[PDB]
Image (cartoon, helix red, strand yellow):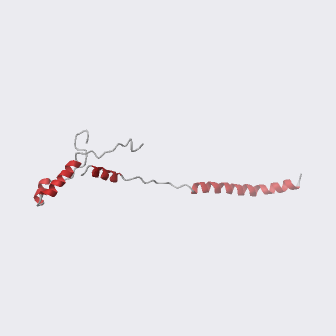
Amino acid sequence: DIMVPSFVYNKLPVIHFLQEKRAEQKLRRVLDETYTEWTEELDQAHVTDAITRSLNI
Amino acid sequence: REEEGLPGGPVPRINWPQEYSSFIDREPVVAKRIRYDTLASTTLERDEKQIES
């Protein structure tokens, strides 16, 4: 009725602070894993060159 | 250009009357004319519906 309740009350602020940091840590890691991915596609000039060769030019 | 009617393919900026005088032998000049006249008579275009698909 008295003792355990008081010590639970004492624990609340630190646990709240640590869990807020843990949540921020998760969000930070989520952002850090994001990285714009640029793709490379076959240049059309080689297509235009193969087109020309096929013509027997 | 297609609406106007000009050749679809690129055309170089050449003056073949000068090239004939420059070169001694006609064979390379005639070959160049054949290549460019064939190039200017072809449409270097592909279907960018099928390509995108």
**Residue positioned most to the right:** A1
Percent across and percent down for residue A10 are: 80, 57
Q: In the image, A54: left or right of A42?
A: left
Identify the residue at image location x=79%, y=57%: A11
In the shown orientation, is residue B25 left or right of residue A38? Answer: left
Residue occupying image coordinates x 81% and y 54%: A9
Image-quadrant location for residue A20? bottom right
Q: Nearer the viewer, residue B21 or B4?
A: B21
B16 or A6, nearer to the observer = B16
Left or right of residue A43: residue B18: left
Can residue B29 be seen at all in this image of the molecule?
yes
| B49 to the left or right of B27 | right
Any part of residue B14 in sight: no
In the rendering, at what x and y percent does residue A56 appear?
Answer: 25, 51
- Residue B51 position (above or below residue A19): above
Tally the numbered discs: 0
Q: Residue furthest top?
A: B3
* Front position in the image: B36 or A37: B36
Measured as percent of width and height from the top left, residue A32 is found at 57, 57
Picture coordinates of residue A15, whole percent (x, y) = 75, 56
